[PDB]
Image: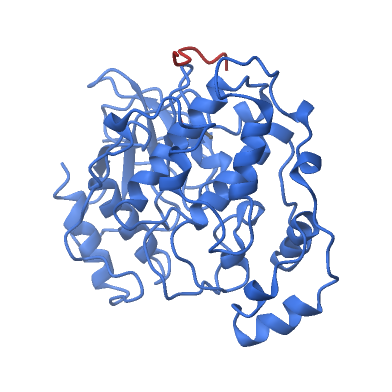
Length: 9
Length: 355
Ligand SMILES: Cc1nn(C)c2c1c(=O)c1cc(Cl)ccc1n2O
């Protein structure tokens, strides 16, 4: 798959 | 080092920590987000509100530092530095702590609308973190959204060890510390506690990440129970037989509760759009929860079993899950203790060493 990389706080 | 006025207790931090400002309150201390010019990286500073002016709160910190020294993991905060604003063992009465400042605490994403993968990954991480301590016989007993920070890139880290430790034969009589909204049953009822109680929290957490509201609203420890059993059916007689003598009667005398089906406690909608990209589907997080959100202390899932479970499985990279558990010397026993004075020294045995 993949892994998330960003997280819009 | 200098000082800067804040709230009531003023600080006494080292020069390498400019533009110093407060960020969070603290049940055990205080914490600012000063810039470590000498290392480049705004750092988080906390000095502990309750040094060792007692007996029951020095033991806590002392245990937190040592755990701090011997910890290390991508999902577990790492000690950056420790310093003391005092000169001789006499004047000793304050221990400050440095550490990498993250982008915000889960209690932020709590109010965000994740979408699996991300959540799916944080959980994993959070899960990974715990796993560490466990795999070395350690309990956090305080995992709660407040003590969970991120970093704008789904990176996560657990924080605070002020009370963490390991046991098996102990009560509490002071749960007036381990924030109850996320207090486990074995905790609440003065029941024994293995070391998975941590997961409980973790559940109430997931709950908090999918409902947006806390999970078990406490009006006093005593009502805590009432609000949980009210949401998980009344525990089985196998469980009952487990409780101490006294707590039993009360616990039985309760108003027998229906309990709810998690298909009902957490209906589809409360779960991120089913943008399926694998074993990631609504019924999965829920399925997981129902393995965590559980009263009996023995029938509730675990870290080991956790990671290796479908809503987590995916990114199970042994490089950080089969992590070599951290160890310690022999200064830790937990149920024992020393003087209300030499405790101070053993603490000094740190601040000095670490510098
Ligand atoms: C609250 C809160 N928000 N953020 C961003 C925090 C916090 C913290 O409470 C916090 C606490 C320690 Cl001990 C270390 C770092 C911390 N960071 O980064």
